Amino acid sequence: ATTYNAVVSKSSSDGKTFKTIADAIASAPAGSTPFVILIKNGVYNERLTITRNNLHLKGESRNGAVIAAATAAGTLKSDGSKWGTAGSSTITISAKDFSAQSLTIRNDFDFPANQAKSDSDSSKIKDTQAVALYVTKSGDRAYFKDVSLVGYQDTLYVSGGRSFFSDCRISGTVDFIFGDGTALFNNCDLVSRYRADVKSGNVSGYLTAPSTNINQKYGLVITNSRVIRESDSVPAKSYGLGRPWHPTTTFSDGRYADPNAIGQTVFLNTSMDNHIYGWDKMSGKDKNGNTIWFNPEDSRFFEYKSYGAGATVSKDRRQLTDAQAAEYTQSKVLGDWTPTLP
Ligand SMILES: COC(=O)[C@H]1O[C@H](O[C@@H]2[C@H](O)[C@@H](O)[C@@H](O[C@@H]3[C@H](O)[C@@H](O)[C@@H](O[C@@H]4[C@H](O)[C@@H](O)[C@@H](O[C@@H]5[C@H](O)[C@@H](O)[C@@H](O[C@@H]6[C@H](O)[C@@H](O)[C@@H](O)O[C@@H]6C(=O)O)O[C@@H]5C(=O)O)O[C@@H]4C(=O)O)O[C@@H]3C(=O)O)O[C@@H]2C(=O)O)[C@H](O)[C@@H](O)[C@H]1O
Image (cartoon, rainbow, N blue to C red; front, top):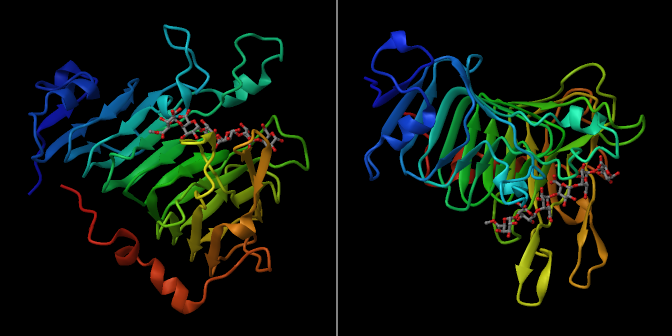
């Protein structure tokens, strides 16, 4: 038995339906009883912030039910200030027990068109991060099943608590899954995108940029998935599995790269095409304002039984033992939370 509290559709011929997703979400009574919204096929040009607990979105189809907006970090607001990376997100989850099923979420910022602009073009944006989905510190127990996330730089921003992505597609270029959250991915296609603006022999991107606090047990955990290239034009050895993001953070002694954000990315039983070269380093600014490099060997970067042409085993690519791999089951990673749909 499954029923819908609200329905969103493009057609007025449907009857008693909402025109926008934002309106349907707003219609929900205040509180924490489950609220389930069906979204019929269509492209909904909307930006959403979810603050109600126990809210659930179900699209008619992943292929056809799309929530999309174009916003880069460097896009300017009315007051002339930048949106910033967090602010660029098409969908922001700032509530508990959210789920989305069978829908696509896009940031439509045209990264390649931006990069193709002449350097003197005042409309050419430097802050090119453009988040599709952001799970915030106030997000915990967020479940995404049969969902497609589309972007280039910084597609998926996972912060705070636990999120679970299942039967999913996620595309991007630089740091397209990033943040300090506990985020588990199962049976997902992670799609590395072509970079027209990157010279032959240089790096096109990085799948992950975890900022997991050293005291947090689990960061980004990718299981039973497929690490694939968008096209044959994506060069061999052009993509890193991860680099360590140490976010600029305000401390008592100033604002600089967080020393204790020693990120975790673990791949288990995941296929990898030959666009993958391994792990990489990442730079930030230290407490003195100097460049500081954070190295993959000092970070929590591991694989277990990778396969496909990108799955090389070497001293630069640490491997889990069977015993260690058993620590990365859904039960262990998500703890007392069992992701369920309404
Ligand atoms: C409640 O939340 C909060 O606590 C805060 O939220 C807000 O802040 C967040 C965040 O917490 C904060 O640290 C800060 O994050 C920024 C940035 O927004 C974020 O996306 C990320 O950025 C990294 C990196 O630091 C950037 O320099 C940039 O990477 C560049 C380049 O863009 C990229 O293409 C690539 O480059 C290629 C090669 O790798 C390179 O060697 C060279 O050859 O160039 C190549 C090229 O093609 O350009 O890597 C570059 C690089 O490594 O520098 O983008 C990455 C990324 O996308 O992940 O981290 C920074 C940071 O400062 O750490 O701001 C966030 C925000 O939302 O704005 C609030 O502001 C805060 O007050 C607080 O509330």
